[PDB]
Every structure is written in structure tokens, then in C-alpha cells.
Length: 138
Image 1 (cartoon, rainbow, N blue to C red):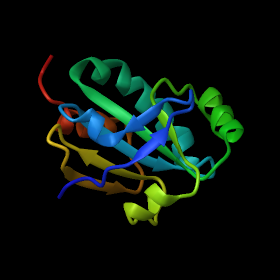
Image 2: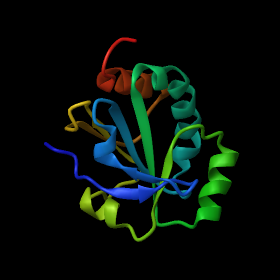
Image 3: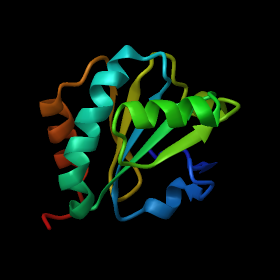
Image 4: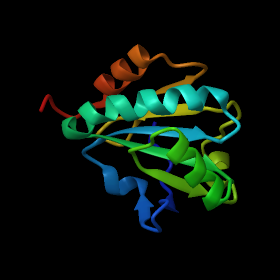
């Protein structure tokens, strides 16, 4: 199943188009600052990304309708080191038909969804999910 394409701005104002990431595995995470699990999971994600960025895994962490200030505050408080984009009007959340937050779509280098994850993720689970979608062994 093809992952719905979208264009959003990242927290530095850079245009990110999902299809631009083909050839990489994509860890597509929907979240808000009201997700107490994200306070746990974002540091885990950041920590795993130190390894998986150079294995061809990209994170796209889609913030669901919050202001740039509230998103920046959260990224700083929780040591985010990965791309975060602003779904300001929730249209991307709606296209993915996402209800429970956080929700993660694991997308392969071919641009297909291989797994949808809801509920809590341990750092071990995050490691294995990234391993699932990485394009090589680099």
C-alpha cells in the first residue's frame, strides 16, 4: 500500500515532500505535545537516529496542528535531533486517517507502508522498527 504523498514545512521553514525520500526507509510519526508517551519516545527516537541516520533511515515527525513556538519548546525540552514538520491544519493526519496519537507509519525505500504502529514503543521496539525499514546495511 502506497504511502499518501504530502508536502509540509519543517521547523526551519524547509519544504519536505514525502516522495522526495524514496530510496530511504521512513519512520513517519504523528504526535502532539499532549502525548505523554512522546516525552519518553522522542529521546529514544533521537538516540536511535544517531545510528540509523547513516543507515539510510529518515524520521519525519509530523506535529498535529500546534504552533511553531509550542513545537520548538517541546523539541528543546526533549532533545529532538531529527526532522519535525508542521501539519498546521491537520490535513496530513486526516489523509492518513490517524485517530490514536502517537501513531507511526513504517515506510520502506520503495515508498510503501510496511507496518502501522500505535501504542507505546520501547527503545528496543524503535531500534527493531528502524532495522525493518533501513535500505542497506551501511
